[PDB]
Length: 55
Length: 55
Length: 55
Ligand SMILES: *[C@@H]1O[C@H](CO)[C@@H](O)[C@H](O)[C@H]1NC(C)=O
Ligand SMILES: *[C@@H]1O[C@H](CO)[C@@H](O)[C@H](O)[C@H]1NC(C)=O
Ligand SMILES: *[C@@H]1O[C@H](CO)[C@@H](O)[C@H](O)[C@H]1NC(C)=O
Image (cartoon, rainbow over all chains, first blue to last red; front, side):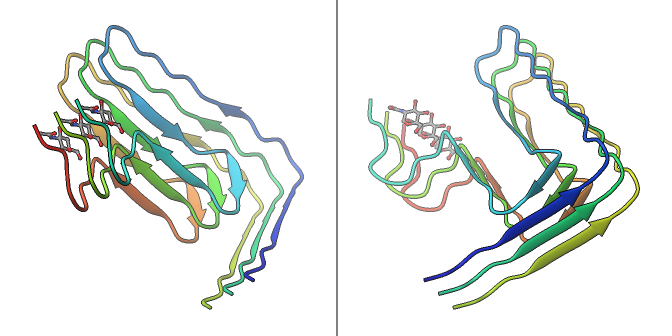
């Protein structure tokens, strides 16, 4: 029964620019956070928890 | 029954610029945090917890 | 039943610039923290906990 609460108050501007390039690469895993982020945030990329892939 | 609470108060500006390049590379795992981030944040990239991949 | 609490108060500006380059490399694992980060933060990259990958 866990409760939550989030609150944010910004007044001036927030510029936020991202760029990602990949040329002739075999793999590129990227995770960029936000400019003003308040609260829980979970990211999972190319993970394997149980009974993975077989070949 | 764990509860949570997050709060943030910014007034001036937040510039935030990211860039990621990859040329003819076999692997690139990247994780960049945010400019003003308050609260929990979990990231997992190319991890293996149990029963992984087989070849 | 562990509870949490986070709070932040910034007034002036927060410039935050990141850059990552990789040219003809076989591996690049990177993790950059945020400019003003308050709170828990967990990162895991290319880790192996149990029953890993086989070849
Ligand atoms: C198994 O799964 C992972 C990601 O979960 C993937 O990268 C890999 O190519 C897979 N391997 C096989 C043998 O299926
Ligand atoms: C197993 O999984 C990992 C990531 O979880 C992946 O990098 C790797 O290519 C996989 N290996 C095999 C033999 O499937
Ligand atoms: C096993 O997993 C790790 C990452 O978890 C990966 O780097 C590696 O390529 C894998 N090795 C085999 C033999 O699958």
